[PDB]
Amino acid sequence: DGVDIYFGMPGEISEHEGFLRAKMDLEERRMRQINEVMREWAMADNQSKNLPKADRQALNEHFQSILQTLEEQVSGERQRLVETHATRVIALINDQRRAALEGFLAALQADPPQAERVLLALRRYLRAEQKEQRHTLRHYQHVAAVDPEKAQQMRFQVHTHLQVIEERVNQSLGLLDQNPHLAQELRPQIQELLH
Amino acid sequence: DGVDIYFGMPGEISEHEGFLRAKMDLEERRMRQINEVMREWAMADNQSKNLPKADRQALNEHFQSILQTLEEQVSGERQRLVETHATRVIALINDQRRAALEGFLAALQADPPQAERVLLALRRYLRAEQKEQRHTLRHYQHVAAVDPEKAQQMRFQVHTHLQVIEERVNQSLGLLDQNPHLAQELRPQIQELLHSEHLGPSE
Ligand SMILES: O=S(=O)(O)OC[C@H]1O[C@@](COS(=O)(=O)O)(O[C@H]2O[C@H](COS(=O)(=O)O)[C@@H](OS(=O)(=O)O)[C@H](OS(=O)(=O)O)[C@H]2OS(=O)(=O)O)[C@@H](OS(=O)(=O)O)[C@@H]1OS(=O)(=O)O
Ligand SMILES: O=S(=O)(O)OC[C@H]1O[C@@](COS(=O)(=O)O)(O[C@H]2O[C@H](COS(=O)(=O)O)[C@@H](OS(=O)(=O)O)[C@H](OS(=O)(=O)O)[C@H]2OS(=O)(=O)O)[C@@H](OS(=O)(=O)O)[C@@H]1OS(=O)(=O)O
Ligand SMILES: O=S(=O)(O)OC[C@H]1O[C@@](COS(=O)(=O)O)(O[C@H]2O[C@H](COS(=O)(=O)O)[C@@H](OS(=O)(=O)O)[C@H](OS(=O)(=O)O)[C@H]2OS(=O)(=O)O)[C@@H](OS(=O)(=O)O)[C@@H]1OS(=O)(=O)O
């Protein structure tokens, strides 16, 4: 138990993979739980054709009540799973951006900087920022797809988030602009990457 | 263009896969549109840092209105995709069930009734029923997490629906009564089948 939780998922299993699998295991488990309740309810239905109405009514409430508890257990479980996954995705995106940023700095702070090395570290950094950009747009696109009202409310926040990302890229590039020659040299190579 | 639509998706592609791929193409398409509007909106703020309030305000309302419209298009388009997919799934499930029932009946009516085939046919039929059953559960199960209020309103319907299926199955198993003998040899094997929690393809 506690020990298995500590080790957690094996390294051979990615977050995405483990996430789908946990989602599948949870769904499969709740599908069975619900089915059992439904069959008990059906069995009670057959058995009670002749009890008085008040008792028939109580039986119905009993099962509708058990199902409510189950539906609420289901919702919480899902919400948590979805919540955890979203957090790990954001963390991975931030971690990759920071890693790439450090790599870009190193290449820049090299006794004799190397055009190829700097350019590739910059591509890496730009890609991490783009992945944050895609992620921001996809989340918004999705809420718009399933919840119009909710999408209208995050609209301005998304717009601002994309701006925050752009400013980070301009500021990070500016660092390359601290080396005129290097800047000019990578100019056409840089532009292609941005566009 | 009309011709390609007549043909529709290749038979090789399942309804589930086509649906998924379609959802993904729409996701990418819409993400690109939204990105263009956001870029135009950012660019506008920039060229408006030295203008009158009213004008700057009207800019906000302009781009936010374009997005309202875009959000509405995305939501409607998604509802249409989901409706089409659901209607086809329900059709697909009824079709495979009816096909498996005919196959089970044809193996029971076979001049020299062969157990291997009768049993296998029964399995395909149970698998078709299992499929409708799981779909009912899985759906009710997802609604329960999305809109609890709506899940509460489905309870009875699901309960009734699952009973319909179980009763259908018992009725269909009643076809093995015309041949009380065959039922014997198969008695055990059928018992295990109906007692499973889930039937995959087999071995
Ligand atoms: O760092 S990675 O380039 O490996 O990307 C991992 C994260 O990418 C997502 C989507 O992020 S997004 O770009 O912001 O939209 O999923 C992407 O990768 C997974 C597979 O990851 S895996 O770890 O190497 O197993 C793909 O799933 S799958 O198709 O391989 O089954 C996604 O394809 S798709 O989402 O099904 O279309 C792929 O998306 S994408 O092609 O990059 O657009 C994140 O998952 S997500 O946020 O739930 O969509 C991944 O974050 S994660 O923590 O690794 O799960
Ligand atoms: O061509 S099919 O009619 O078989 O459709 C294939 C897709 O069916 C799903 C989902 O259902 S759907 O939305 O109606 O398409 O899975 C379901 O069907 C497959 C095949 O079952 S079957 O009727 O014998 O053909 C089952 O897989 S398996 O049991 O053969 O291993 C699924 O059972 S299970 O979920 O794997 O336990 C069955 O799910 S369900 O309970 O019937 O809803 C798609 O897979 S799914 O999206 O993971 O559910 C199939 O897509 S696929 O391209 O065929 O893989
Ligand atoms: O009306 S529902 O409550 O069922 O909502 C339907 C939407 O649910 C998503 C996920 O929404 S999310 O939680 O906001 O991310 O899809 C999920 O459910 C549908 C159908 O659910 S059900 O009860 O089985 O019928 C599944 O479609 S289907 O495969 O069953 O045909 C989704 O699987 S699939 O990838 O679409 O094939 C299932 O996704 S998941 O397994 O939960 O990850 C929405 O899809 S979404 O674009 O991923 O958000 C559904 O469509 S919706 O029109 O946006 O509501």
Image (cartoon, coloured by chain):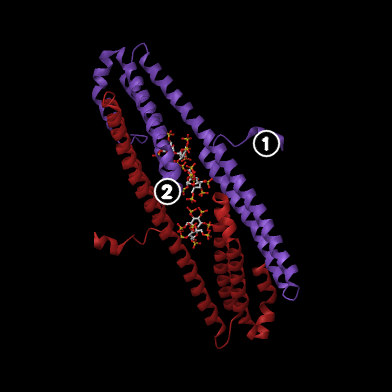
Chain colours: A red, B purple
Callout 1 amino acid = Asp
Left or right of B149: which side holds A33?
A: left
Residue B14 visible, this orientation: no
Q: Which residue in the structure is indicated by mark 2?
A: B145
Query: Residue A158 versus residue B131: which sits nearer the camera?
Result: A158
Callout 2 amino acid = Ala
Q: Which residue in the structure is indicated by mark 1?
A: B4
- Expressed as whole percent of the image width and height from the top left, the position of residue B131 reads 41, 33
Quadrant into which the C terminus of chain A falls: bottom right
Query: Residue A14 versus residue B170: which sits nearer the camera?
Result: B170
Query: Residue A93 versus residue A181: which sits nearer the camera?
Result: A93
User: Can you tell which of label 1 and label 2 is closer to the viewer?
Assistant: 2
Q: Is residue A57 above or below residue A169?
A: above
The 10 Å Cα crowd at callout 2, few under 14, some 14 to 19, many 20 or more, is: many
Badge number at residue B199: none
Q: Rounded to the nearest whole Å, what is the CA distance between mark 1 and mark 2?
A: 39 Å
- Expressed as whole percent of the image width and height from the top left, the position of residue A194 reads 65, 69
Residue A45 visible, this orientation: yes
Q: Is residue A54 above or below residue A9?
A: above
